[PDB]
Image (cartoon, rainbow over all chains, first blue to last red; front, side, top):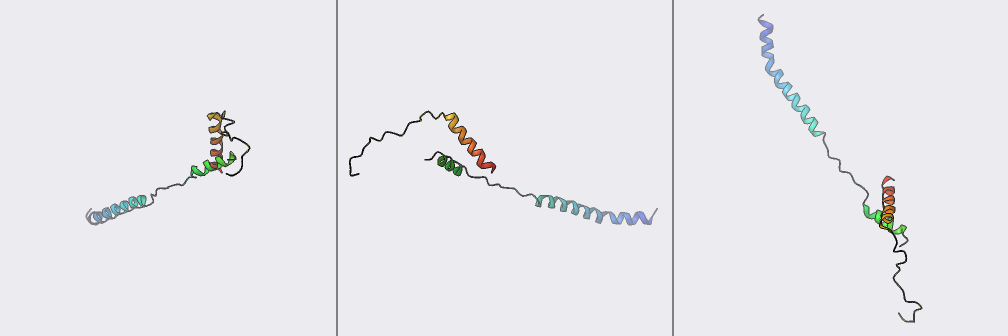
Length: 57
Length: 37
């Protein structure tokens, strides 16, 4: 009725702070893993050049 | 250009009938081919 309740009450703030920090850490890790994937595709100029060669020009 | 040439070179237009449809079509076939490889 008296002791354990008081110590739980004393615990509450630190645990709340640590859990908030942990959630912020999770969000930070989520953000840090995001990278934009710029792909490179075969230039169509080569395709045009091949087309010209096939024509025997 | 010394020397009398034998011919009056005409424009090489001989197959002007190269319907844009089939001309572009073959280009697309080649284009799709190169990309897949």
